[PDB]
Amino acid sequence: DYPKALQILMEGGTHMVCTGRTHTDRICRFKWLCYSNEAEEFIFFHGNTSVMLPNLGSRRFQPALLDLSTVEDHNTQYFNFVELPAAALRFMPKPVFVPDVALIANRFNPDNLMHVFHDDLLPLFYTLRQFPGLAHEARLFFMEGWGEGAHFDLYKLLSPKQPLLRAQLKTLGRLLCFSHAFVGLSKITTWYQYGFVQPQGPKANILVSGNEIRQFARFMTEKLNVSEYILVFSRTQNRLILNEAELLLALAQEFQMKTVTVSLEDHTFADVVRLVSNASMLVSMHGAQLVTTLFLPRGATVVELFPYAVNPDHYTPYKTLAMLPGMDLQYVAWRNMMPENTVTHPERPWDQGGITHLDRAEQARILQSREVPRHLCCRNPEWLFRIYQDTKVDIPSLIQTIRRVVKGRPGPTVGLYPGKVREARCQASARLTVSWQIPWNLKYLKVREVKYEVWLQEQGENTYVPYILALQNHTFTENIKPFTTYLVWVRCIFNKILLGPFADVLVCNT
Amino acid sequence: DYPKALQILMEGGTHMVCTGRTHTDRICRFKWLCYSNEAEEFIFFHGNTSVMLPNLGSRRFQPALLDLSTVEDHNTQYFNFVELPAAALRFMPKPVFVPDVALIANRFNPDNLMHVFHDDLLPLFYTLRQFPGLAHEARLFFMEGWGEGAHFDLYKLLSPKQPLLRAQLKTLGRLLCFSHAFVGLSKITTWYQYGFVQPQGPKANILVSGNEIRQFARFMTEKLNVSGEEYILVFSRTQNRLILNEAELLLALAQEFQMKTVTVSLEDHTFADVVRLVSNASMLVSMHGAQLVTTLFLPRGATVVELFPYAVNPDHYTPYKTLAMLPGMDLQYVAWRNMMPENTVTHPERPWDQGGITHLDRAEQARILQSREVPRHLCCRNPEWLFRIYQDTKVDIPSLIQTIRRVVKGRPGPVGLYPGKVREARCQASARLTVSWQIPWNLKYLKVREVKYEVWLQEQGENTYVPYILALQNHTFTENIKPFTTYLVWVRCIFNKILLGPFADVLVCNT
Amino acid sequence: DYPKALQILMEGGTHMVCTGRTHTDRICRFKWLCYSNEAEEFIFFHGNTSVMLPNLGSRRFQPALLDLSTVEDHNTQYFNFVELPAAALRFMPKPVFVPDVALIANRFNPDNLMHVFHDDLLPLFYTLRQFPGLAHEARLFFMEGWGEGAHFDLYKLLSPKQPLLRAQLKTLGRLLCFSHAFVGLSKITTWYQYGFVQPQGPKANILVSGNEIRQFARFMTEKLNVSGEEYILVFSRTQNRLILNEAELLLALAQEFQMKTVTVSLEDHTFADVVRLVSNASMLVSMHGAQLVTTLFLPRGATVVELFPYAVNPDHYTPYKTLAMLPGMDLQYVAWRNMMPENTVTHPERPWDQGGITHLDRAEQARILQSREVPRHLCCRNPEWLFRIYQDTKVDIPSLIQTIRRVVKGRPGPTVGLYPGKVREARCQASVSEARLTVSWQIPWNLKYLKVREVKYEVWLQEQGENTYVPYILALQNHTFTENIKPFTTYLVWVRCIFNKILLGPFADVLVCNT
Amino acid sequence: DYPKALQILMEGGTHMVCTGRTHTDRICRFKWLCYSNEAEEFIFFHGNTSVMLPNLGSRRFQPALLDLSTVEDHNTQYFNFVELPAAALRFMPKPVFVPDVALIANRFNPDNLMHVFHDDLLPLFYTLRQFPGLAHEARLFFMEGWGEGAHFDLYKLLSPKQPLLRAQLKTLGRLLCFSHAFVGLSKITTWYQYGFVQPQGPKANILVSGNEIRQFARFMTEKLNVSGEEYILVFSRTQNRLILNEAELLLALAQEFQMKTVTVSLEDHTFADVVRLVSNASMLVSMHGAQLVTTLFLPRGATVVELFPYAVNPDHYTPYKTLAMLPGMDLQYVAWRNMMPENTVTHPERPWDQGGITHLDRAEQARILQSREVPRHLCCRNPEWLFRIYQDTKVDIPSLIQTIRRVVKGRPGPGLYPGKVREARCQLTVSWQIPWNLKYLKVREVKYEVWLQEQGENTYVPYILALQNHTFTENIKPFTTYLVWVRCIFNKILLGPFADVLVCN
Ligand SMILES: [Cl-]
Ligand SMILES: [Cl-]
Ligand SMILES: [Cl-]
Ligand SMILES: [Cl-]
């Protein structure tokens, strides 16, 4: 009923329970959270059942309750509400109730394919799957206040319900109340930051592997109803490969493989995914189209071309993605280092990398610069000048660079850690004997190389002495002193690089 | 079906999606998470749908994926699993499937009422309410490996399903798989830390208010079927940590406050009776101890009087003080300290766990008996703390009554909203800087006693800000304002001196 | 059959299996061990079943296989045999077979009641009870070559079979063979040595308690057909070593201790009467001598008052003191010494063997009469010892009563003494700002079923490397060491339980503990 | 009856009477000795007939009352009880009574044939025969807490009653009481010590001869129902410690000693078959190992040939040498040592218990492979000893045959002391009658040793005479006192006892 709902709200109030310690990792589950289209402001109504966990009091504004976006820009990211007593509904319009459960988020830039996938789609995908029901029942509300933008068709693949924008809320009524709303997006799937504080680069601690990216890739291919060769990403407008035709022959010749071109302009996104999905190698100028890297099969190679004066190590979103553990991709960066081979466009508008709007002394400085200096966001004019350059690729130079990584023809465990060693014993005679059972999970496992690392510290000292043994039982003779206390740590190693957990330390007396 | 479930698991694998940046704030939602009773070890099975978000690789063991307990003791807190390929189920016993959705947690100390409420019940209550369904459908699994303990009846009030302990899992089969399990507990409702690293005291950043405590109190009263004549309630103890002069105190209080006085006891009353009595008490008097956690059931306006024995400094032991003084709890708190050794009775001949000291060297016993105040200390079983906390106490009535009266003038017994942003902030420079703004939107529907505006003025470049508290929506800055300069201007609304609202978008103003 | 037995022996041979590492503690079980009365020599016959365990080869003669007596005099004590092939019986007389199982021992001095009980009866009693059957079936053979002597009636109480002496063996035939013989006597029940090597005194390591003495006492009372009004019993002597003032002493004692007083005498009473009287006496007063060995018949709680004549130091002559003060005997012991020469009567004109001295140099006679204390000495019949021990004595009653009263305050007359088990499940544990070592244990298993007045625990604490132990007596099962405990050190911790200060239990396995 | 037994115990108590001065040589006869399966502890109940001889008080724990094992390892060896008043049975479970007489002992290692025979079977055999009845009536209780182990069939040959292990006691009830139990084992039949304190080797003073070993051998053959054509018997091994050239050795021996040659194997034969074969062998050839303890079954006159692998020194490992050379065993013993490294095969990759060394630091592995002789060592599983003892061996036939031939010239195959001299007279002229037992005896060489000490000095002057009468002239001084001892000697080495000293002036 409406008169039922309106009383639940009028006496009960808003109910907020959020997971996370800080605003950076917070996702809030609300009941009877309301939105004034007049005020353009979310509303928490204090009633007699009303709960606000966390209760930050005035730290709610330092800087905000929640991040609506994954992109830490100190602006679109922030969600906050404004407080009223539920009583005050009497002096206010009649609420319109949103009945179906909502996920309320912000899109940083729904015109850019990298932003769309990295910032929005992968987060939305796994944020929905954090809370039971949401995935198949939730309607997305985008409150940042952009239109559908160039890639809305992709957003629409996440819920089976039509997402709403802020513009569309204005029409629905002057006062909206969500019966059940989640607000915020996990940042767990992010790997890159666009340089708001220090210059752009990979996140310090990446918590997503290839596996979880591929599982999202599977879902997106199937929802695009789309289920050997080198694939070259073309651009028709700007940031061109001036010698496309030469490159297509050179690659075909060098790698003994068919070569296709694909274009975001000239193909449905479904076609792009169909083509990227079975490509053995993907060649592209640095740009948003390379985020389709996440659709490449295991074994494929990414070749990223950078124009004159743009240093590949300063611009590593697609490098970072390709080199994630479990992505099983190879990555090559090639840099145009020959000024004869670049075409600049200084007469263009400022937003397309033009420089005629600047002092003549700055224009000079920019044209003399052989490398774009490191910089903060956003729209740095030297970065734009260079990134909107058209490029003649030096084929011999490209092929050398690819060949340093791809020896032979390009194209096609899960990586389990061991358990603790069990029942670690030690024993003296000066001889120290240490023994242990295999880790429990090893019993049900075939692993090529299985070693045990044993650390030996004389209590008092900080010197550790490592040993890699193959057997479950070893007797230390060398450097072992009588009437001494030894601390002994032990861990199992799969295939040299998968280090398992250490068992409880052993105290051993000689 | 079983053969259905077993295939979903055998080819699909375990699916893990967790909220939170570190192991400290992580709660994980699992599908087809399994537990070997042989190995005493949770199992993640890698299949072809299997997801592990976060994927920490080897940082999963530094120190763990999750905290199972709210109590950061670096031991019971830690949840981890061991990895297999789903394939490997063929070489392994037949799974037993837990069909109903599970919440898997650890209890720090289910024998202590403070630990039970603070560490377990309030966290369980609000962790369940984080995820849709869980509250009314979830079966709790306690993996720490205690028995029911003294307060299991209270745990049982949270789910309508019988909670299971680790001992009971062993019987169910050699290999358990949860179709749907949440693991971990929010620490958001905690207000105290028991001194594992630095000495015990309140959490530095408490994120729970009286509102959220009371809403949990309502739920627990209703589940205990328990819902002119006002009274003072005195918590008695029959075993140890006695008030030697109970009868004297009951008369003194009655006389001083003109109010009936009842005693209640955890030993001599069902917990439902305790809550019935605490629920309508105008004042609650108790020696420091777990029984005082029932403070959270007191009505708005009531007073807590906490008595500390000889050599125990109230400010070193503040769990019940912290709870009573939480914003929106609307309780008053008094600490009284026994300062007179003639009024204490020590018990040094008792077992170590009841504060005895005869188990120590003779020189330590001396040191302890000579000590006039328990020195600050880390967890846990500090022998001087136990010696003093298990003292019986003759309360100096005149001293108690004076102490209460410094806080409770008259008879004991029966807002909080922040402003919005100021709107449409304008500035204008004629050197004179004029700044103006509309009231915050929510002020329109609000009656607040004192409403001020704070204006910060920063010359762009400098880190000097210059604050001003105005009453009016319009001010003109005169001296100190330089011509041909850029000023940044922040503005926020303040309710009743202490409720600081958010700052509006900065203004850039040029002179 | 005889022709059966004779073949078993003629082809089979002697069979010897003995318990013990040395001749001092050896008891041998023989089959077809033989004795030539002509040669005065035991014979081991090597046949085709014949066994000799131990096989000492030539160490059999260094000095002997076995001790026949408990008394280490290096002579009567020794048992040995001589070897022949069983074949050689053909060139030798017809064996006479002893059919019943034998115990073959030597008696050191069967004319002396102390020697009889200490050396022979208590050993025979418990040696018989070492081997199943023997007690009720064994005939004793005494090979030392004394007659019955003054106390044969007592020997006869041990087996229900008439013991045989060496004299009687000579008649039986020129060649005897025991079908089944035990040889030797346990020394386990001995508490005294008569000073063959160093001067007489208690054995250094006594392995018998009151319990095992009393159980032998019970047996001997029952075999003697003997089992407000409490009394003091005074052992009199009619011949020598007299109390000259008996009548005075009997009144003085009666008066002082408010108790009837009886006299008893080995000469004037059947041994059964002596035991009847000693068995219920609250106090036993006697001159030092063999009659005081009847001390072993006193009830729990009684007091022994031993009188020594002039110049005899009680601490030099402690067989009856040692017996009375054995654990579990629960007797009190008083020694009184005649200190006043006016109160002794010497007898220097008697034969040398009864303490006479006229057979010595006149300078030695002088030296002996001038001597105020018999100097310590070796066995046997030292002439100063005999001169003084055969003295008659007027007892100084005031002096005696003072001496008794130092021990018997109030009226004279009326645990088992169990050791604890190991402490169990001994744990230890450290802290991490200052070093604290916690040690705990469960009570010993047997404590569960036991009420003991004082129960303490002794804990020894050794820093590994040092030899310094540091002891502690605790009352509780759980202690935390703070003092002198160093961080980053290894401590060895021993723990034992103590009942009533003096019953020290076994140590548990050592704990290694790290700080 | 049960209610009879229970009263005898409840009022009477435990009764203990033991033979021996120390714990090393003690055997105890108990009545109403009890065992708590809960406490894992024997119980002495003090009643009113109760006897405890010896009463060591607190020396009962220094270190123990008794040795349960013959093997002095300071652990399995020790038997002790815990004391209660018989009264306390009221607060305790209902006793289960063992009615038949018991012998309670510990087995050191019932998986090893040498340990089984040397430590357990021979001791049990002669311990039972120390006390009348026991042999034919006793049930053995093994409290060490091993299973039956590989040789239980042999233990079962001693009593006619099924021996019990500690595991099986737990089932019988919470509280067991033996009506009649002997506890401990004679060490009198032991000849070897396995090196717990000083390195392994023969006991310094061996108190058992071949006679007593053979009498035990006869008993064990009869209980195994096993009782021109002569032969050499070679002990083969299938698993480890192999003779790599068995076939060559069997032909060489056959040809050299003109004699059939059989192989036997503990794996491929019932122990009864092994004894059947060893019992009539003229020569027994084996690698050093437990199988050679079957030496005690060889006939009088047979030869034992013990082969030691590379770097194992025969003189450091002498249990079978010691056994073979016991007086009255009438065996010949040959030790051969593999001296040639080309003729050994090591197995360092095997598990540690089969002589592997891959579990050690790399510098120890080096040290071990460089070593030409296993250094002397204490018990137990020394890794160099194991490395070498699990070697397979190609036997140098010429070298072996040389070694055997130093002792067996021709074909292989098939001790009384005197009495005292009597009536010793002196006058320096000294005379004596023959020892009594000499009258009934034919001895090849019969000499007399006379010691001559001038009273005061400690110088003795020995003389070996053939006649019963001699006159000393040399170094004899007038107006002196001489002490004269005299003993008879059979065949140079059997020294008889000395007669009573003579004083001669
Ligand atoms: Cl779902
Ligand atoms: Cl709900
Ligand atoms: Cl008997
Ligand atoms: Cl027999």
Image (cartoon, coloured by chain):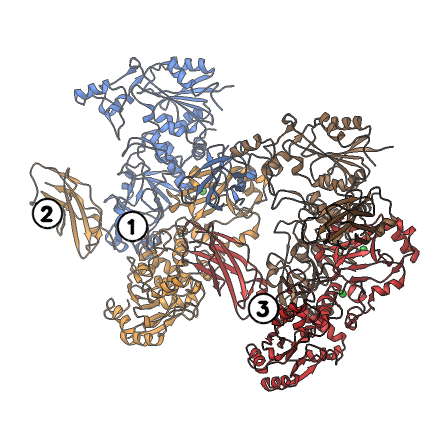
Chain colours: A red, B brown, C blue, D orange
Q: Secondary structure at mark 3?
A: loop
- The chain letter under disc 3 is A
Q: Select label 1 or label 3 by which is in front.
A: 3
D46 relative to D270, above or below: above
Mark 1 residue's CB less than 8 Å from ligand 4: no
Q: Select label 2 or label 3 by which is in front.
A: 3
Amino acid on which the number 1 mark rests in the picture: Leu
Q: Secondary structure at mark 2?
A: strand
Residue matched to label 1: C56
**Looking at the image, which is closer to me, A314 or B60?**
A314
Amino acid on which the number 2 mark rests in the picture: His
Whether residue D96 is visible here, answered yes or no, is: yes
- The chain letter under disc 1 is C
Q: Secondary structure at mark 1?
A: loop
D415 relative to A280, above or below: above
Residue matched to label 3: A445
**Looking at the image, which is closer to me, D104 or B91?**
B91
Query: Quarter of the image holding residue A256?
Result: bottom right
Residue matched to label 2: D470
- The chain letter under disc 2 is D
| Dots 1, 3 in contact, CB < 8 A | no
Query: Residue A115: x, y in percent?
Result: 72, 68
